[PDB]
Length: 222
Ligand SMILES: NS(=O)(=O)c1nnc(NC(=O)C2CCCCC2)s1
Ligand SMILES: [Zn+2]
Image (cartoon, rainbow, N blue to C red):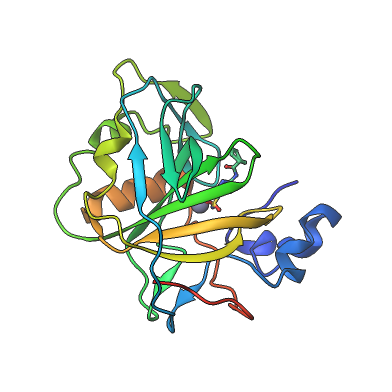
């Protein structure tokens, strides 16, 4: 079932496109969000266990995605271990800090041993070229399709050494907009060239950010 971010199947509409997309419009704990007021708490430390792996790079029509066939890239938070499935990108940013939208956002999507989903978000401010992403941008499929990268890729290089985060509970930002997703949103920003962002957008064919959704009852810890 066709969906996108412009025209007639835009997010404002996802709910009605089929009956299994319905939480997109009826959900009360939907992502993304504007992080304005927060509650200062002592959050458990992120331990990252990323290493180089043989990824491959996909334009699925909505984002540019880096798929991890094997485990081995994990994340430990508060005892539970969370395995990296893929990462992908929204231009511009989906989530906001104090009303501010960033040139780009990355999403590291994990599953624990119970299939409880965790998204680890990185926010990219304007600046110099991102040299650590250049490897993905080079083979970036500019239409729907998959290219399998010859050289191992190391996502360890895409995360900060400083790992403070915002913690709220949410949903997928894409249909079926499934809830029960944990959102860790990192505070130390990375950077992108304007050229890297235009090129992403060429590939995908539009701005691929879902508008922010009401927090309703939710507190964002920081
Ligand atoms: N825009 S986003 O909320 O971060 C999203 N992230 N993942 C989304 N779906 C997936 O990853 C599927 C494939 C592999 C792992 C879970 C299910 S949607
Ligand atoms: Zn995403």
